[PDB]
Amino acid sequence: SPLCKMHHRRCVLRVVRKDGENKGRQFYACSLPRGAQCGFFEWADLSFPFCKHGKRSIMKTVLKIGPNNGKNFFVCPLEKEKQCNFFQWAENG
Image (cartoon, rainbow, N blue to C red; front, top):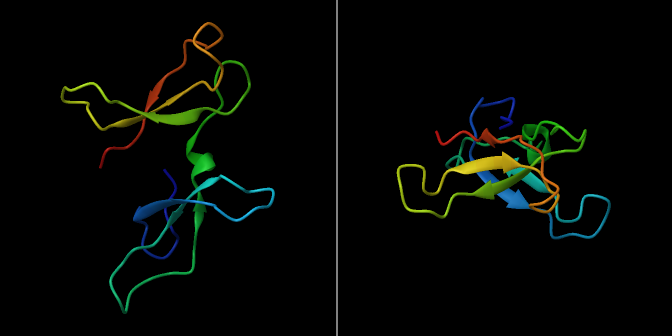
């Protein structure tokens, strides 16, 4: 995932609710305590590599109980029958 340039640390993930070309995009922001923060924001789309179709991957979450429950992963945005054999785990720490 991307990191802000000031703290080199992932802090929180937000979604753009404003309309515009970036409507619905995911981005990281700082959630450090008062006194420390940065006005840097990072597009979370940068964390998704290309998939085998030459299209951006998207984030989904594991809902199945197990040691990987709650972990996020990257998969293809096409439907199950048109997905590529491309899967990547996202950082859980």
